Image 1 (cartoon, helix red, strand yellow):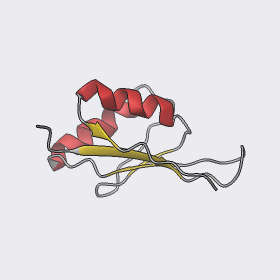
Image 2 (cartoon, helix red, strand yellow):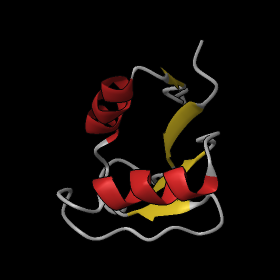
Image 3 (cartoon, helix red, strand yellow):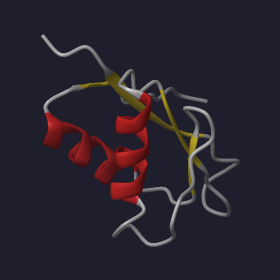
Length: 83
């Protein structure tokens, strides 16, 4: 009962120096995807752009990402791992 899963990952390069955020997987209508990325770029600090299902977001706020995601009631895939 959802049809759509958003997953936010953070490919950092160390402790603190430069982190990136890639948003992809949102299985939803194409026009709907543009509305999602447009909402995050509305009040997140830096207008992020989209790229054929690939929205680039510069910021390590994965925590806030899981929140806005639970706002729609869809599923999420908080990525992670120990390295």
